[PDB]
Length: 51
RNA sequence: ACGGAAACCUUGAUUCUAACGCUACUUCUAAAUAAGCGUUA
Image (tube, rainbow, N blue to C red):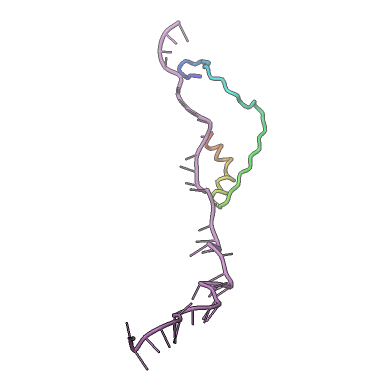
């Protein structure tokens, strides 16, 4: 989608993708204190990055 | 027709017994298989 053309143009690039609304679990391990603050702040940093 | 003749420096003996080329040590450290879609129509 181009902001200049103001329309969406399709391209020959087809991918195998996970469908929307799929639940996938990850485990994250932290061995120090600073990284613990970083990972406990993964939300509100994701929000700041998205803002 | 010689201070000469005859006479083994010889027999039996394991350079042998015991003794770990052993003790400790992460092939380890960061890293989205990902980015760009212009211009014409």
